[PDB]
Amino acid sequence: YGPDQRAQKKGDIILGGLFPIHFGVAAKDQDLKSRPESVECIRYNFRGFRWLQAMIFAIEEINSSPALLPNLTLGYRIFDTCNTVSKALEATLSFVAQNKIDSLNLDEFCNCSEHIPSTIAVVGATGSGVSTAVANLLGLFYIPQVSYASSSRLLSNKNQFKSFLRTIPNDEHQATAMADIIEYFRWNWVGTIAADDDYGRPGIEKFREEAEERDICIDFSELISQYSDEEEIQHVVEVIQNSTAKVIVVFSSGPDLEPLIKEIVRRNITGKIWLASEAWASSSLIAMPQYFHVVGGTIGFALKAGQIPGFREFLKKVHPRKSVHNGFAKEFWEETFNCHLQEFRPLCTGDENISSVETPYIDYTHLRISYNVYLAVYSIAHALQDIYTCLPGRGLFTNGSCADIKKVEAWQVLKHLRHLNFTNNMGEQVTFDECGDLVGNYSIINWHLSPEDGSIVFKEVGYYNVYAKKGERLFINEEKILWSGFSREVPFSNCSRDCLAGTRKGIIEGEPTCCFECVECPDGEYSDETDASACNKCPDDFWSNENHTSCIAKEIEFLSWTEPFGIALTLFAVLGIFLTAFVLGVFIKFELSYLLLFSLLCCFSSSLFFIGEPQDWTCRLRQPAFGISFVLCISCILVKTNRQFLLVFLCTFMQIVICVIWLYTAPPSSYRNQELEDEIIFITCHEGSLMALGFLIGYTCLLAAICFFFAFKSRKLPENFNEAKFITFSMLIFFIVWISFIPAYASTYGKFVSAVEVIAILAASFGLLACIFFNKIYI
Amino acid sequence: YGPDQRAQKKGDIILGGLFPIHFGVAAKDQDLKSRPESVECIRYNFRGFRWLQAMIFAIEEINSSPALLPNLTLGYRIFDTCNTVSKALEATLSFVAQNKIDSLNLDEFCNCSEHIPSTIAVVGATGSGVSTAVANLLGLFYIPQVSYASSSRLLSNKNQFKSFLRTIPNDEHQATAMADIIEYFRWNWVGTIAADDDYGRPGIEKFREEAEERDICIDFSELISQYSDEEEIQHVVEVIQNSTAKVIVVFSSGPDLEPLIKEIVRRNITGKIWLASEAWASSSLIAMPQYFHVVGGTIGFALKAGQIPGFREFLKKVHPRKSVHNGFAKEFWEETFNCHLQEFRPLCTGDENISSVETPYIDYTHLRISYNVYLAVYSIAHALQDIYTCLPGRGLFTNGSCADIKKVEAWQVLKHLRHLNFTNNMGEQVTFDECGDLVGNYSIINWHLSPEDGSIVFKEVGYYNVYAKKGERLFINEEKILWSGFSREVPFSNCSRDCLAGTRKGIIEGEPTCCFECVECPDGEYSDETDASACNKCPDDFWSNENHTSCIAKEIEFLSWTEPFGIALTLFAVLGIFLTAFVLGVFIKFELSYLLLFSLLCCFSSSLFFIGEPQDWTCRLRQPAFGISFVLCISCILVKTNRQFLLVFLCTFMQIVICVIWLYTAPPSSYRNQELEDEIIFITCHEGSLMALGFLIGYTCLLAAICFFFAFKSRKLPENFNEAKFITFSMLIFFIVWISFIPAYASTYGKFVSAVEVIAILAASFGLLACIFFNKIYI
Ligand SMILES: *[C@@H]1O[C@H](CO)[C@@H](O[C@@H]2O[C@H](CO)[C@@H](O[C@@H]3O[C@H](CO)[C@@H](O)[C@H](O)[C@H]3NC(C)=O)[C@H](O)[C@H]2NC(C)=O)[C@H](O)[C@H]1NC(C)=O
Ligand SMILES: *[C@@H]1O[C@H](CO)[C@@H](O[C@@H]2O[C@H](CO)[C@@H](O[C@@H]3O[C@H](CO)[C@@H](O)[C@H](O)[C@H]3NC(C)=O)[C@H](O)[C@H]2NC(C)=O)[C@H](O)[C@H]1NC(C)=O
Ligand SMILES: *[C@@H]1O[C@H](CO)[C@@H](O[C@@H]2O[C@H](CO)[C@@H](O)[C@H](O)[C@H]2NC(C)=O)[C@H](O)[C@H]1NC(C)=O
Ligand SMILES: *[C@@H]1O[C@H](CO)[C@@H](O[C@@H]2O[C@H](CO)[C@@H](O)[C@H](O)[C@H]2NC(C)=O)[C@H](O)[C@H]1NC(C)=O
Ligand SMILES: N[C@@H](Cc1c[nH]c2ccccc12)C(=O)O
Ligand SMILES: N[C@@H](Cc1c[nH]c2ccccc12)C(=O)O
Ligand SMILES: *[C@@H]1O[C@H](CO)[C@@H](O)[C@H](O)[C@H]1NC(C)=O
Ligand SMILES: *[C@@H]1O[C@H](CO)[C@@H](O)[C@H](O)[C@H]1NC(C)=O
Ligand SMILES: *[C@@H]1O[C@H](CO)[C@@H](O)[C@H](O)[C@H]1NC(C)=O
Ligand SMILES: *[C@@H]1O[C@H](CO)[C@@H](O)[C@H](O)[C@H]1NC(C)=O
Ligand SMILES: *[C@@H]1O[C@H](CO)[C@@H](O)[C@H](O)[C@H]1NC(C)=O
Ligand SMILES: *[C@@H]1O[C@H](CO)[C@@H](O)[C@H](O)[C@H]1NC(C)=O
Ligand SMILES: *[C@@H]1O[C@H](CO)[C@@H](O)[C@H](O)[C@H]1NC(C)=O
Ligand SMILES: *[C@@H]1O[C@H](CO)[C@@H](O)[C@H](O)[C@H]1NC(C)=O
Ligand SMILES: [Ca+2]
Ligand SMILES: [Ca+2]
Ligand SMILES: [Ca+2]
Ligand SMILES: [Ca+2]
């Protein structure tokens, strides 16, 4: 009863089933003026008819093989749910009719003897919005429902759907796999689209939850349906166009993506790569050749294929007349041959060849969901077998006493179906968990266009092994992947382009972490990585390059010790020492000959002892350059004609006491200065407050000035061949040198702050011997 | 029939109803050894019994007032769904029993005359996981279901739930309101918790979708249930403890938050503020006084209260004996008085006072959902009224012919219920939209503890006007809000603390945009805002401050025009001019008196014409400082005793030709230099390649040196009171000055690169007159 398009066959134990022979109900909506009537289904699903044949075929195989359920035949009352909850509930209200005694004792059948004989276990409700609505009605009467296709995670809640097992993997793994793919191809800017029913809605939240532990920032997220209006479809395609993201993760069903794909083709939005859910990655509505402008390269998923023997030869044995136990055969015949079967449209002779036309009923390469239908009805058969072959004192019920077969109930088959452990025709073990589902391995496919009259071929490009360890589960042989149909290079679908090794990452306000700008950082930056979020600072003896990469450029070494700028002045000091020694020899052979020669040679020999990079001793040894000058300027008071002479320690010991007092105040330490930035590693010796200045003013500007007022009366007096005149000329040379010293010493730094003093001491002590020794010798 | 705890009363038109008298079914799960039986409900819901009394009371009011539905009495078959889909489906399978002809013609009642008289419109299914499961079964038979409490957005899909209207607002507005509150209090780091059924799951996705257009980054998102296990509850409280976010948006129901709230109290996780959904913000399971350590200050929502007259006096008229049409009264009596009614537990006399004990059945301050029950049954009455008072040729059905009352069907009441426009007892208009719901205004409450024996009082702190414009809908009078129970200051719940105006925002890799670090930016930074994501760069005449805020510090103005460093040298130049003029007057009164006085005064008067900030003319007027020196040094060849003399243009015109050729090569333009960074706005005049150097070497070092070999034979020759000797002394002064000029000119910059040349010209031209004019005058 119920609907009047059944597929019915009597038997001892009646199964029942629910299959999607059409794709939907008609678009007519009632205004409720007239009394409402049953809505008529519109499209046709040859894949759904193949699923129905796979159920019926395995029931004939169980009734054929006598090693499984002997002297007991299986019937079935297979209905058709046109992918709608109402058409499914009209069927599963006729499934539970004899069981409807427990609340309504007022059934009292009164229209049949066996009273619509009680279904033991229903196999069906493909959609997950349909299984959720049928498993609520098959949960009061405890009839087990073994669904072959519904694969949402809401149905794995065994406090509400108390009797629901399924032979298709959960979708907690597929939303992990679609994040592993996006992580593996190094994308971080994707968008999601999900069908608004119980399949896409809790299956895109798992992808959102598992693509933010990988940094898979989501761009947009829209929900579609198969009954959405034109404003909603236009809004979804405007969000697709208004964005810049090439990976679109579509977690939807077959005919829910149809109004979006039609309109995206009609508006020609090319470039995106569609990661596909399992429900539409092998679909005879989206894989159509004229959609291949926008739908190509769609890396999808598919379940593990099966092998059913004799099934393809059983599919061709169909007929609208020889099949008396199949009410859908006439509708399939008329829809596949464009006939009109008589018992615009020509009358059908009924002698056609089924292998002649091209249709998804017989043009298939792998059984994937049809094998799940076969496996579900074999699961119910292998539970009825264990009820059949149970010995007393051994079973599963209370006190081990198992139940009979001739009066078997639905909850006993549910109890045995929970504890199921059997083997297929492929040697695999099938067992339902505590949440009642199987576990399987996905085989990632790709959408290629066959270049000889073929529609679309699905080329397998890897797997997804769910048994392996977390992290190593995905294998993508990416030399078979044709990006957007024809290309070969992996497309760029990041948000902002990853900047180079000279720049850092700077963010925009109101945009995610996955989108930045990239600016350069200054002054000791050294962005050593490629995408560093903050470039560091260099060590103090290093400075950044021109391209702002790793700072291998060190700072200065400004010393000029043996350089060709200081070595020539050292040669001048050696020439002064040699010219002094050649006069000392002529003064020895041929106190003003001992001290005013020895300290005079010291003032020109220790003046070469202030070059190079200074240190503690080379920074404390600047005091002899004045202490020896104060003793070598004693000739101006010792060689005069106004001459008890060995009391030069009335000034030399004063200078020595000044030096011994000032060596603690002006410290014996070079001080490295930071005046420039790039190459500024200095050494400047940092005289304290007044020490060397007071020492110079009290010796080298005081003795030569106290000699000045004493020799100004003798400058116009020649004596001993004008010795006073030559002393005054050397004193004028010394005054010119000490006038030239101080401003050039004040207005220089570093390399040129010592080369003024060391040149001025040379220029004074060379004149103070060349004006005097030559005139005293050559006369 | 169905369940054997009904509330039944016969009548002409039977309504039906579904109410949550208990809170859930017992925790016993079947192992299916025994034959499974009906599970027994556990807790009690006095609020649910108040809702049942509000339905029954309005049915008595319709049967009482003769102005509404006269000569026609309303019955009801009210059942009890213990918040479970299975207990609701056992009831709504006994609602549709006479309507079960359309698919099963084999009903053929055979146990009643009227055959369980057909319910016209059911009122119930409070939960939104229960209304979704009952509206699928009341959508084949087109019975209208007017739910009073289910408020999810999945039920507003009129292609699947074809007959479902409701008198509670949708939850597309409440998830907007909870984002408006978080935006209004300036939070950006929240966490969400949602009950895993059809209420929290599509209601937290709307909050996630509307709290990322406001930048409301989400921290965590967990799903709970009332059947969750201890590992899941421990995981949720470990995510709450392991996070740092104080705003927790709980979108859940009453008894779904119970195992989380119990365990959070048992582990004492204090500090969080719980934004509440409407379902538990006024709940007699969470608002309990011992939970107030962690549950306080919970800014919730509540619907608009109603006024039902006579209802509180009707509630006290209940009795287990006088109520013959109410099967729940004995259970309510026994559960509220701890009795055991006879027809551990003492026997009940049945003479107690209902207003004596404290219970949520009678301790209420505002009718919110009870008014919705009243409004739903008045909606069905005001649709039956319009079927009653329809004139022919005027109705809503086909060709205007409306239907009778004595044979009325469910789809006619559905048609009239769609077109409903009536008025309450409060003067408000009630009309269902095209998606079949009402619109209402929320009244935001807060959870205060009453400090005299009270449990928890709910103090209203504002509203949420959904009729107003988008953006201005929320009004929070925040001087009534007690944060976490007692406090008064708004709590800080951002991710990272907003940094100051000296620093920028730097990001962390692997963390959202809402969390940053804050580093300082250098060298012309001027972070003018408070939380700028990138600090700008200053204009070139400005440099950054010490605190790196807005750069008001301008650069240098190094000129020294009228400063106390250049004005004293200008006074020295004026003194040189005056001392030259006083000698010119004594040479006039008492060509070497004309040219060697006029050009000599020019060389000391135009030497003050090179001070200040230079410009085109003040940078081209450096050439007279050599052109006048070459003409004023002509005295050294014009005043000698070896003296056709007016051919000084054999050198002065050569210098003039050099200047006229070099004024284009060395350009007349000051060049601003950038040698330092902070205060470095310079002017340096940028001599070209060799122009001034060659001019100086060809005039001022050439004439004085060609005079040298001519006057070296006359230096030992006194003539005209030693004029040659005084000329040689002035030439030695000039040679000393031009030896002191060049190194101090080379080793300075800017302010000290002109003050060396302008001092050296003064020192040369003062000596070249003071050595000569004084000896020529005073003799
Ligand atoms: C889109 O943005 C992505 C950021 O999420 C980029 O992903 C980055 O790719 C890098 C390779 O180009 C990865 O570097 C790897 O780092 C690990 C250590 O973390 C090393 O062992 C690997 O050797 C190294 N890879 C190579 C080739 O050297 C980054 O780790 C990775 N970022 C993250 C967060 O994982 C994408 O590159 C970018 N897209 C494009 C096209 O550039
Ligand atoms: C948590 O982070 C939030 C960032 O999302 C901070 O929110 C910022 O608060 C500022 C006020 O303190 C807002 O400034 C306002 O800016 C508008 C113009 O955009 C002006 O008209 C207002 O006058 C100005 N407010 C004041 C008081 O001057 C920021 O706009 C706002 N950020 C955003 C993105 O809106 C929170 O402040 C922060 N929490 C705490 C406690 O600081
Ligand atoms: C799951 O997928 C994997 C890979 O696609 C399959 O694992 C292989 O199984 C064969 C047969 O046992 C082994 O010889 C290989 O070594 C396996 N590959 C590995 C471990 O990488 C497996 O057949 C699939 N199906 C199931 C049910 O596990
Ligand atoms: C919705 O909420 C608002 C504010 O809580 C209420 O609006 C006020 O209504 C009264 C009566 O009409 C007016 O006098 C006020 O001016 C309104 N306030 C405004 C416009 O800010 C309103 O009563 C609530 N209910 C409905 C059904 O709108
Ligand atoms: N899991 C799918 C059902 C499904 C799997 N494969 C399919 C192929 C076609 C149609 C539906 C399916 C759903 O929830 O809807
Ligand atoms: N909308 C709630 C129903 C509800 C509203 N208020 C309530 C108060 C108590 C219990 C349930 C409710 C839900 O979907 O579940
Ligand atoms: C798309 O972008 C245009 C231009 O900014 C804008 O006008 C339009 O509203 C956008 N549409 C959507 C859906 O964002
Ligand atoms: C869509 O665009 C592609 C490439 O731009 C082009 O080949 C194709 O013909 C277009 N189709 C339509 C219908 O505009
Ligand atoms: C043993 O089995 C009988 C019926 O088979 C049952 O009534 C009884 O309770 C059982 N006893 C135990 C201890 O299991
Ligand atoms: C039962 O199933 C388990 C795995 O689920 C398997 O290891 C075991 O071999 C099965 N039992 C038998 C008897 O095959
Ligand atoms: C909480 O933090 C601790 C310490 O880092 C960690 O060991 C634990 O696994 C965390 N738990 C969760 C649920 O994040
Ligand atoms: C929980 O903590 C609060 C404050 O720390 C304290 O007042 C209260 O007594 C605690 N309760 C328990 C059970 O530890
Ligand atoms: C008028 O009404 C009759 C019955 O009331 C109906 O059969 C007929 O179709 C209607 N005609 C029009 C034009 O509405
Ligand atoms: C019908 O409802 C509208 C608003 O929905 C209201 O404006 C109008 O007044 C109502 N009709 C009557 C007759 O009150
Ligand atoms: Ca398909
Ligand atoms: Ca934003
Ligand atoms: Ca409650
Ligand atoms: Ca991260």
Image (cartoon, coloured by chain):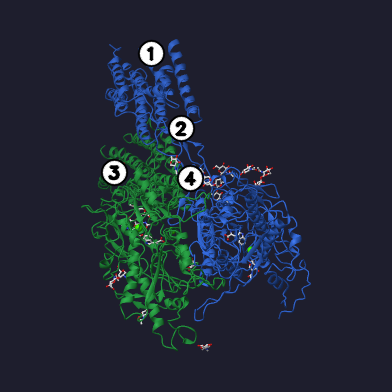
Chain colours: A green, B blue
| Residue located at (36% from left, 60% from top) | A278
Which image quarter holds the C terminus of chain A?
A: top left
Instruction: Look at mark 2 in the image and give the residue it sits on.
Output: B558
Q: Are marks 2 and 3 in contact (CB under 8 Å)?
A: no
Counting residues from the start of the chain, the first of labels 1 and 2 encountered is 2
Which image quarter holds the N terminus of chain A?
A: bottom left
Q: Nearer the viewer, mark 2 or mark 3?
A: 2
Could you say which disc has been placed on residue B593 in the image? 1
Counting from the top left corner in percent of width and height, residue A467 is at: 35, 70
Element type at mark 4: loop
Could you say which disc has been placed on residue A690 in the image? 4
Element type at mark 3: loop
In three-dimensional space, the C-alpha distance between marks 2 and 3, rounded to whole angstroms, equals 33 Å
Element type at mark 1: loop
In three-dimensional space, the C-alpha distance between marks 4 and 1, rounded to whole angstroms, equals 50 Å
Counting from the top left corner in percent of width and height, residue A730 is at: 35, 37
Mark 4 vs mark 1: tell me if same chain.
no
Instruction: Look at mark 3 in the image and give the residue it sits on.
Output: A565
Counting from the top left corner in percent of width and height, residue A236 is at: 42, 47
Q: Nearer the viewer, residue B187 or B642?
A: B187
